Image (spheres, helix red, strand yellow):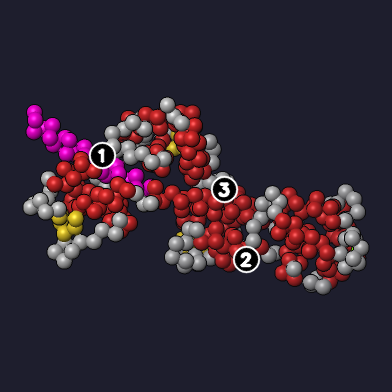
Amino acid sequence: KLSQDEIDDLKEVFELFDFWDGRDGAVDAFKIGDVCRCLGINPRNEDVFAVGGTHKMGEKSLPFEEFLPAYEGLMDCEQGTYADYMEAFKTFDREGQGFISGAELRHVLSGLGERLSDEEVDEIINLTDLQEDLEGNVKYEEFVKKVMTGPY
Amino acid sequence: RLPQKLMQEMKEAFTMIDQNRDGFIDINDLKEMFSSLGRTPDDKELTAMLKEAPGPLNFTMFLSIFSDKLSGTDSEETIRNAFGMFDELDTKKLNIEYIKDLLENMGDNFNKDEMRMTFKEAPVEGGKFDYVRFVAMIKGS
Amino acid sequence: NLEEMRDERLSKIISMFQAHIRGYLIRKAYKKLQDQRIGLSVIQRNIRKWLVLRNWQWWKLYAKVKPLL
Ligand SMILES: [Ca+2]
Ligand SMILES: [Mg+2]
């Protein structure tokens, strides 16, 4: 199933993360999610836990061979579509015009689901250049597209 | 390894020390070079330096003596930009806790003894590691 | 049970979106992570060279000679 092209990318990334926790041929089980994110997949935290991800640095460490199957197991995780995202945000849109207030945007991002930190929230709003208007409203559809299409 | 610009540097260094234009560095070249720079070592220290070469000190011998010790070294600029990598706002400093962490717990970890000798004489003030000054120190004793 | 199912799906959809944000943040940082890897190799290797070579008389000479060219 896994293209050799893909196995190569996994090695490259694996070695980067190996280096970054102390070169020794193993990546911390806590960084499992991030390796995979670098490879272009978007697992929920609950996914990476199901494949062996730990809650904290220093509990377990994986050599490449134990890591490959973790990756293969997340690779098929469910990923949100744009339609799903719009439906979700629409439940917070009070008049269905396409706006949501910035405070609400922050409530859903750091108060629901797998809650993101204030720092993480401020950063995605920064990177996506999402501005609110004079009454504190933002268009969730722009934000959704910017996040989906990625940093490049 | 080992890069041309570094080979060109070793060659230029060999050439200046070889005051005779011998093609060999001998004890006279060394006394001459040392005396041009400051205190000149006694003839014992000089001969001991020369005995590190298992033969007449020509350029290929000079290479034997320096190649391994220099092979992985980088210019002052390269090293300052390596530090710059962790200095986003270009303050020309690093938090002492930050650089200690990088060195000790990431990459090719520094053991407790490497950390001790690294920070014995490092220029650190108010929690700030002066990496520009630090680079100067590791390039010039 | 249709109301519980609805709350769960909305909550999963948000989590997937947060997954998308998490993804974006890491990929955003990747390139700098690679450069820093190189940077930190430069720093550790060069400090290590210094520690070995700083009391070696040949090096002390070599370094006084290098600024002259
Ligand atoms: Ca490691
Ligand atoms: Mg000569």
User: Which callout, 2 or 1, points to the residue nearer the camera?
Assistant: 1
Residue B136: which numbered mark, if any? 2
Q: Secondary structure at mark 2?
A: helix
Report the amino acid beneath label 2. Ala
Residue C60 visible? The answer is: no
Which of the two marks, 1 or 3, is nearer to us in this view? Answer: 1
Give the residue type at disc 1: Gly
Foreground: disc 3 or disc 2: 2
Horizontally, residue C7 falls left or right of residue B6, namely left
Of the 4 image quadrants, the one containing the C terminus of chain B is bottom right
Q: Which residues are magenta?
A: C1-26
Most common SS among magenta residues: helix
Q: Secondary structure at mark 3?
A: loop
Same chain under badges 1 and 3? The reply is no
User: Is residue A126 rendered magenta in the image?
Assistant: no
Residue under the point 8% across and 33% down: C3
Instruction: Work out whether B85 lies above or below A115.
Output: below
Compared to C17, does A75 lie above or below? above
Q: Looking at the image, which is closer to me, C8 or A63? A: C8
Disc 3 target residue? B110
| Disc 3 within 8 angstroms of ligand 1 (CB) | no
Count of numbered marks: 3
Pick the front one: B14 or B107: B14
In this rendering, the answer to whether A38 lies above or below A73 is below
Give whichever of discs 3 and 2 has the lower sequence position: 3
Rendered location of residue B69, percent (x, y): 72, 52
Quadrant of the image occupied by residue A71: top left
Q: Chain of mark 3?
A: B
Q: Is mark 2 within 8 Å of ligand 2?
A: no
* Residue under pointer 1: A80
Residue A51, percent from left and from top: 36, 30
